[PDB]
Image (cartoon, rainbow over all chains, first blue to last red):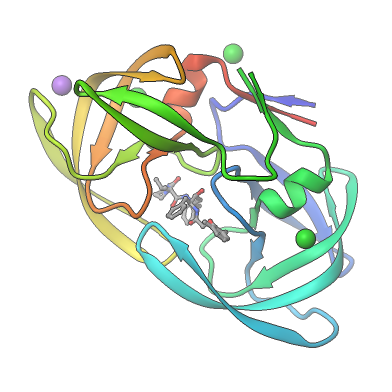
Length: 99
Length: 99
Ligand SMILES: Cc1cccc(C)c1OCC(=O)N[C@@H](Cc1ccccc1)[C@@H](O)C[C@H](Cc1ccccc1)NC(=O)[C@H](C(C)C)N1CCCNC1=O
Ligand SMILES: [Cl-]
Ligand SMILES: [Cl-]
Ligand SMILES: [Cl-]
Ligand code: NA
């Protein structure tokens, strides 16, 4: 699709069989989702936002659908105020910024 | 241009007679620049996200050139870790997300 930016670029994602709303974010290096259960082992990570850094759980090779596009990759889980699809998965689904 | 997302989508901007590098951020409602002087009136604002909130100065009707494209809008100035071009000015340069 071509998504303009007059409103937030929110899409539906599916992860763990569940539908969630998330933001397509070219300013995010990684994907971070609100607290949920994911399979496997996780690794520690810090990410930085407008107000400072938070600790998150890094899950690798997680199956996730983004606006109907299937992806498999790293998902961070933690106390983010909004679900964010970052560049690691935007790149995988072929997204570019155009002007 | 068409910007892929393997790396951060950083571009050069001109604001307040100064050149800066800034992040094209579809996940940002607002444009936030590191501390600098701008002409005219301003009012305080709090913006919060990952990591919490920061206090900024809101300047309205500020012209910015973004990767050679002129726009005008509100610019927030404060202790952001990164200069961010948000949706309020991305729409004005006709930026879209495409996949
Ligand atoms: C940078 C990065 C590394 C790894 C993983 C992730 C998710 C990363 O991105 C973290 C991050 O906060 N990125 C921001 C920009 C970023 C990159 C690097 C350092 C700091 C910031 C931005 O793009 C998304 C984030 C989303 C958001 C979160 C909570 C509430 C509302 C929105 N947006 C905002 O904070 C904006 C600010 C920028 C005006 N914002 C806050 C006021 C209300 N609305 C709004 O839009
Ligand atoms: Cl990934
Ligand atoms: Cl504006
Ligand atoms: Cl448009
Ligand atoms: Na003004």
